[PDB]
Image 1: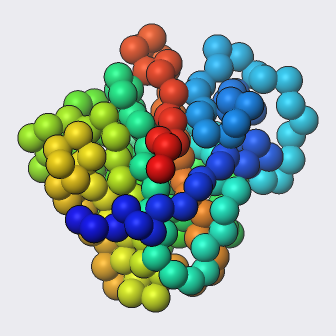
Image 2: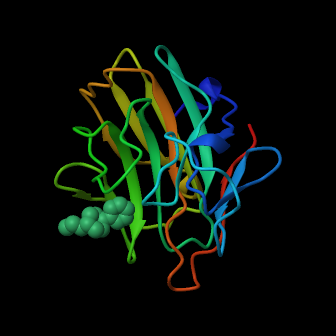
Amino acid sequence: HHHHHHMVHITLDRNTANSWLIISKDRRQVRMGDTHQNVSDNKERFSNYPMVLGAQRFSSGKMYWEVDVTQKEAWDLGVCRDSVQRKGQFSLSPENGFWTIWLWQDSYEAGTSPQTTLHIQVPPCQIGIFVDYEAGVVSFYNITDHGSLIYTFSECVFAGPLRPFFNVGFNYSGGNAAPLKLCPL
Ligand SMILES: CCNC1CCN(c2ccncc2)CC1
């Protein structure tokens, strides 16, 4: 792909984070803490899952960013409507305002309803995310495997401003403490 020149500088929005997340000072890294991180509750926070939004809102144009997932067992990544449900249980689907992929139990899936099997020969250490607002496209690329295509959501009905979306996943196994990191341009 040749999307690198639409690179945008993504930072994480602390106010949207699940209360167990630790976001780095530069707002480019997030990990699961071993306890409540001593913040007040607010209506923005994801309550049930270890999720956080980027601060950036997109309503036009072409945007590209990269996320480091090295040594993680579980994570979700992509974009979502600014207006997604924050509280309680929900599925990651375009009907609920999410355009995501994930790693779970040694398999990679796209957040369709129902979910779609991905075919990845080289486990990614970095993921590229490309959004074309006007075209209605979200695409994911395997940076570790020379930028090979992982998945394209097309005919997307965004129906609002988009935000970068992250889930560091639970760490019940003790094998998923590693952070998500926004890679430098
Ligand atoms: C058959 C239903 N399975 C559910 C549990 C596992 N899952 C994930 C795993 C990781 N991130 C998001 C969703 C899909 C829904």
